[PDB]
Length: 167
Image 1: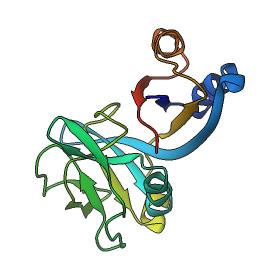
Image 2: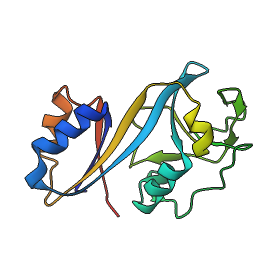
Image 3: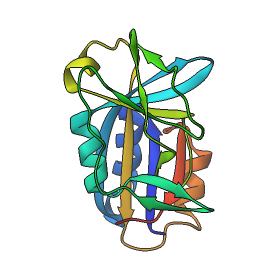
């Protein structure tokens, strides 16, 4: 793996990219809102953002003890947002709207930063008041696992980070 997915405030994610800019060959920033539902964390994004994550192969279905990138985002509409979680969850309500369960899909190669992931229409997302967070994907020119990754984890710029296999 040569990718690192990081989560946190935009400024912390950006500062981290900046620190390692000459070592990074590509990067992607995705905005989401981090909230809670039923004592669990939920990372909420809009359709436009989730579609872009699918194009980077960053939404991955959990399969046995591994992961496989989803190739299409399930249908999203104002009357039917979706939720991804480890187990079936049919009572997830976000901003008064019940989400439709769409399986055990995670960002990157493991469940990090949240318990569940929700995707709602762009118009629905605009109405959610929860704090905005940035999900950053950095693809490194060379293996960053032995020094860069632990330094990011020990640091205080991002809230969470994990190694991932890039597209």
